Image: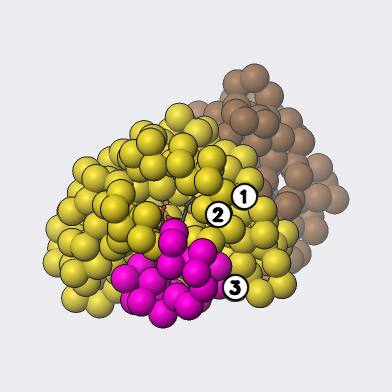
Chain colours: A brown, B yellow
Amino acid sequence: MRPLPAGLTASQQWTLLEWIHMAGHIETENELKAFLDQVLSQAPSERLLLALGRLNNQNQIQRLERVLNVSYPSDWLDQYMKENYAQHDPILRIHLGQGPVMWEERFNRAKGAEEKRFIAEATQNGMGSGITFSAASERNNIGSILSIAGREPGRNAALVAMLNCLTPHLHQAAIRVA
Amino acid sequence: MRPLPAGLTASQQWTLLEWIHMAGHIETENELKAFLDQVLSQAPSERLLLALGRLNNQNQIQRLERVLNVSYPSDWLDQYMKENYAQHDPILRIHLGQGPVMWEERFNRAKGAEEKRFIAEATQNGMGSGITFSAASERNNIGSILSIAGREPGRNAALVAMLNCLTPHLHQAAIRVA
Ligand SMILES: CCCCCC(=O)N[C@H]1CCOC1=O
Ligand SMILES: CCCCCC(=O)N[C@H]1CCOC1=O
């Protein structure tokens, strides 16, 4: 269990409380999307996606079970699927449950030609910067990622901490929905 | 989704946040009992029990699926089972999800001879006063009750509100455990 954030204002504390309270009442994909729309409305980004995956023994996604696009450009997602970027996207290689991953930091460390190709393409599509939160359940090797694209979220330490803490509850909701 | 309480102090708000955060990480009966022990340590009672039940079409328990005794006297539970009090206990007739039920108020309204007998017996065993919180999921007609015995909890409006809000999350945890 990841620790709750220190240094939140009463307003931020209340927002987080509302978010985790709401998340625990999510039963349907409809409710899940509606809730993510609400969370999105509080972040300095316009691009959010949640995915659920079956994991390997190192807590990496080996199979995508559900992709819930909230506000990624549909053209980018279409390209991602069509061009099989799942095989080249460094974000899908994260060890889930090991802490928030900043994309620019992860991208700068990539070495493969195909990975660099993907990064260049993501960059042209306004996806060069962002953050991915994650949670995993070894009850049945299942995990979730919450991705938010942009530079501003990562610079808001409180928001990062809030979304990070929300993530395990979104994970439980996603499992219920699936 | 029941509304979060108004008028909590920052400390009470933080406690509630910790409780719902912790509840969403519960995966095992062990963890569930340990967490309920923690919650118990914050209430002016020493007697707590959680139960999960399959419901009828009016959201009343028709079958008990799991009874997790945290701190009811074992002698009282033994008697309850042995004497089949489930059939006579007004608390097991609550419509789950319809708000916290104060036992003294519910008991005062009982009319049946067997119900009155049970009430008299509960009273002698220090169970004449208390409160039961509840939540229900019509996904599969399943609900939970959280019972706390004593007079002091009901007199602490903040605690009542906090435990009430925690209940749906304990319910989801109980479903995961079962
Ligand atoms: C469609 C699944 C993609 C989930 C992983 C993710 O958010 N990947 C970022 C990295 C840059 O571009 C993306 O789409
Ligand atoms: C063993 C299941 C009992 C759950 C319902 C409950 O908490 N009933 C109270 C009412 C007075 O005595 C009790 O045990």
Q: Which residue is mark 3?
A: A34
Mark 3 near mark 2, Cβ–Cβ under 8 Å? no
Q: The residue under label 1 is which amino acid type?
A: Leu
Q: Which residue is mark 1?
A: B64
Give the residues drawn in magenta, as a range: B90-118
Q: Position of residue A112 (x, y in %)?
A: 65, 26
Mark 2 near mark 1, Cβ–Cβ under 8 Å? yes
- Label 3 vs label 1, nearer the camera: 1
Instruction: Compute the Cα span from label 3 to label 1.
Output: 34 Å
Q: The residue under label 3 is which amino acid type?
A: Ala
Q: For the residue carrying disc 3, how many other residues have a C-alpha within 10 Å: few (<14), some (14-19), or many (20+)? A: some
Residue at the spot x=65%, y=36% of the render?
A142
Taking depth in this image into account, of A156 and A56 the one nearest to the observer is A56
Judge whether B39 appears above or below B112 on screen.
above
Q: Tell me: B151 left or right of B85.
A: left
The mark found on residue B136 in the picture is: none
The mark found on residue B86 in the picture is: 2
Instruction: Compute the Cα span from label 2 to label 1.
Output: 9 Å
Instruction: Compute the Cα span from label 3 to label 2.
Output: 40 Å
The reply to whether the magenta stretch includes residue B75 is no
Q: Position of residue A84 (x, y in %)?
A: 81, 42
Question: Does the residue tagged 1 have its C-beta within 8 Å of any atom of ligand 2?
Answer: yes
Q: What chain is tagged by disc 3? A: A
The reply to whether the magenta stretch includes residue B111 is yes
Taking depth in this image into account, of A36 and B135 the one nearest to the observer is B135
State the quadrant of the N terminus of chain A.
top left
Q: Quadrant of residue A75?
A: bottom right
- Label 3 vs label 2, nearer the camera: 2
Have a look at marks 2 and 1 and say if they share a chain. yes
